[PDB]
Image 1 (tube, one colour):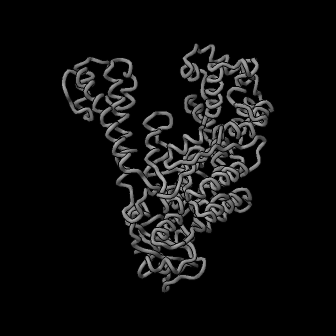
Image 2 (cartoon, one colour):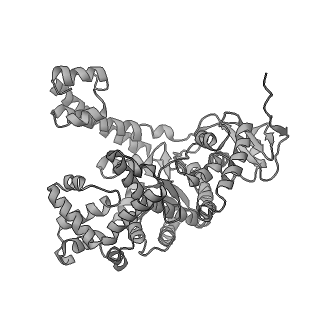
Image 3 (cartoon, rainbow, N blue to C red):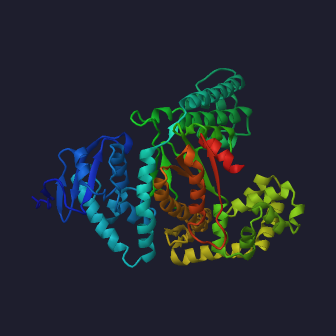
Length: 540
């Protein structure tokens, strides 16, 4: 028989100052959860709270794994318990593949279990280990102290505060989408010659392959191939598209209004993504359509409290400004410095015509490359998007890199340094490991290259936004305003109607002045009763 493992020593609540917390929720969403257990740990000693909710009052901060989530629940219960140290944040800075407590425990030692005392002891141990791993990493430590750890309190406020929704609007939008779905379904039935359950894979296989005799398997991948093969496949794809938007971004939202707050509590996570951008859940704001009429309409459902207004701020051409800075391209920097329309000025440079001779077609081409260049868009993709011959796409790309040669040089150098070193870095020194740059299979290596030279751009953009949020938040609290949402290049605030103007102007200032680049940062801002209106004002 084996020796028994060391047990945690246990002492009475409350714990001493600086203790690490562990906690178990009834479900993962803290705004919707019951706090089932609360423990704290210090120097191989664990303190279990007899009634969790009362025990929160004894803590000066939430220090441990998922600290932000405990802070959100505290805020829901009317208690201002700020998140402090969280080993998830350390692990994520060490390697952004570290996104879950179970993964971090597996990698760096211990085990993520369902018992609050063990989670408290795990938190303590993980912090010690990961803090040790970050010794002599000055830039990562600075990012931790100045961005990541303060940002966790900002995220707790956003999630706990939530956003008001227009339920009547959402019902009206739902009906409109239902009408379109019904129209498409009816067409599909006519083309098939009989009704069937469109959502049934078996029934749909019969129709496509056995009845219509289309080439032979009913996945979204499969139907994409056949999209042009028969008019019915196009209709099925649209039906699936609309059904998904309705069931993902429209119908669930009213049920996510919390009965106690009357608001939707979007869940924000700062250790979830490859690039370091913040991610959202319930809803995933990033997946709301941007361009389509339906996508814009969903944002009209997000409204301000009575007597308040939303303020929507967004960085203009954030990625391209970062690329100008990182590449040091003199021509690209000059475009931004001189403050003229970036895409027009780009077309002028590209086509060797004066800006006054730049036509819509030229501007559209310049704009497509200005966005595609960030992601490694191929000449083939460019030719498809502009509906021009491949050869002409190639010519445009050459004109672009003739105008902006250090952009091409920067791309090449980033991949070269990435191969040599095994990682790429943001401006603030966040590293992402990119082992597939040396992968044999050409397919996978090019996909890796695109993700690699994008990380400095999008990762830097994320860093700038996160620092802006950290700098802005206490100024907003002073003014009696709120920070609600972040997605893409954009930040949404809520302000008392009479303070909305002053909030907008201050937020624009803070965001534009967050960090000095070789080019100015530019932020557009709009004010409105709903998010879509605020965005429409900002684009005006």
